[PDB]
Amino acid sequence: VDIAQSELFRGDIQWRSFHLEASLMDALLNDRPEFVRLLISHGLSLGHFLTPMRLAQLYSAAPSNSLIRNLLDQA
Amino acid sequence: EQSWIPKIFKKKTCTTFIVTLCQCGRPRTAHPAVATVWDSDAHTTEKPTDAYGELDFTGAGRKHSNFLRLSDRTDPAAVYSLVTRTWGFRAPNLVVSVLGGSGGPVLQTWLQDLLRRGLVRAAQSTGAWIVTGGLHTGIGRHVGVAVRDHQMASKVVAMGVAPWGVVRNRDTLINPKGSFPARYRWRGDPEDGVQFPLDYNYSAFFLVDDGTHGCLGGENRFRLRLESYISQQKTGVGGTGIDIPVLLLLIDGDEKMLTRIENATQAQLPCLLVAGSGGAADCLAETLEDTLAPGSGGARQGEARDRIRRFFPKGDLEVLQAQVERIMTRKELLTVYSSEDGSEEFETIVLKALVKACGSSEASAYLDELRLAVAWNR
Amino acid sequence: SDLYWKAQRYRLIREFHSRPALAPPFIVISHLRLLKEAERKLLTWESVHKENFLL
Ligand SMILES: [Ca+2]
Image (cartoon, rainbow over all chains, first blue to last red; front, side, top):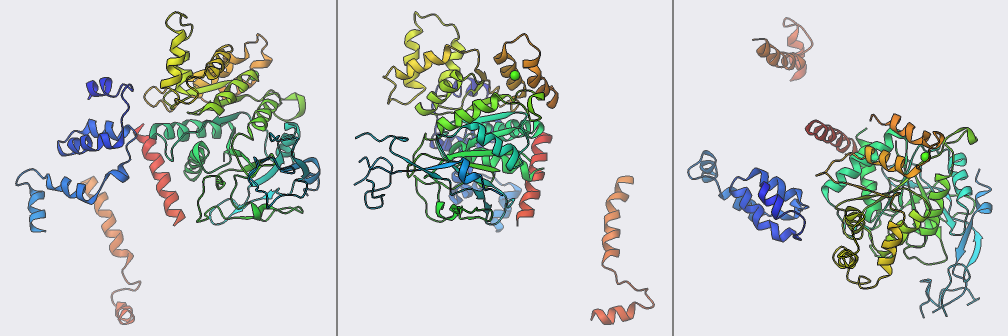
């Protein structure tokens, strides 16, 4: 994350909320804690970001035959 | 108990007509029968003020908000005497005048945290004053929610100056005999971009009347005049007290604010600018970072910043560059607050700014800054 | 064990909190008789302390 913050988030590049929505999903799906903290910290509106389709996508990322995955399958 | 208020204060009306629509925003049909280039003072009529009183916001609130409408051409001395004596407001140990536009309904989370944690706690600790725009928009709203969040987590005297005309529900404030009971429809359903509601977190309201139906920048003259008079005032008890430091906090802004800071610096008032605020405020911070940069390769850097740190309109114009040059002519007064990845601590910055602004060997001039150093724990 | 006793102390108090006020020999008559802004302010106060603790 230090490389990304030092290079991409040095302030020279003008970012946008939609420019980070895809990356935010990737960090959440790939278990990147420092990145989601960094991405949200850079003025990202979480309330408008989260959608029921996105939430369903997040729960669909249960790792293989995990215990949680079994509960959704039963549910 | 407010008999002198209509007498020692005045209100401004449009009077003449200077075009269907004139410059005052009040159209031809609704106009006095007394009806080139409009003049705020030559084309206005002075009448006794008829909007003073104590506002009581509907619902949650302190049931006390002293709001007064006063003409622009008024001495700040009378206003300060009214606030300190009649309204019972204690003489402030510090006055912070938050300035800026802060374009956008929302601001950065770190910026909001610095406002709520840094400014409000520092104001609360020393019993300071926070003078902002008395409107529920821009920086005025942001400081309003910061005060409200701190208050409910525990007061802080934060008042607002707003032009007369841009205030919604101005019909319920009119009572020449006094508006001590007053109900405000701050939650009015209709929304418009020329009239904004008053925040419910401000202890006092100063409605600047200049004979217009509503615009921006009509309170700048009174705002600077009030700040300078307080800076040249003692903390009560007559002359036995010490001076009251006055500091200006700047976040973002536009061309109108750039004149404000230049005028304030001309008025010998310490200024404080925060890095990363946005356009028209980081330009000064970057120019401070260059400091005594050489003219060769740096003279055009001003115009480069004019186009990248500010909007394209007036960027090619060198009038703003002249304003920049005038500002650095007294660069000792103003200082920059480094974000430091969200320091949320600027009492040291304020103390450093105030101590460097005085520049007097006499210990009397440094008494006020000493008390603030005592009031805070640094 | 000291932690366990402290934890189970709440269970004892809750059990006796809802018990009828009379003694078991006389408990029959008791059995026969048997048959906003403040919340938001509190949460903000808690949240402020959380950020202070984290900082
Ligand atoms: Ca001083």
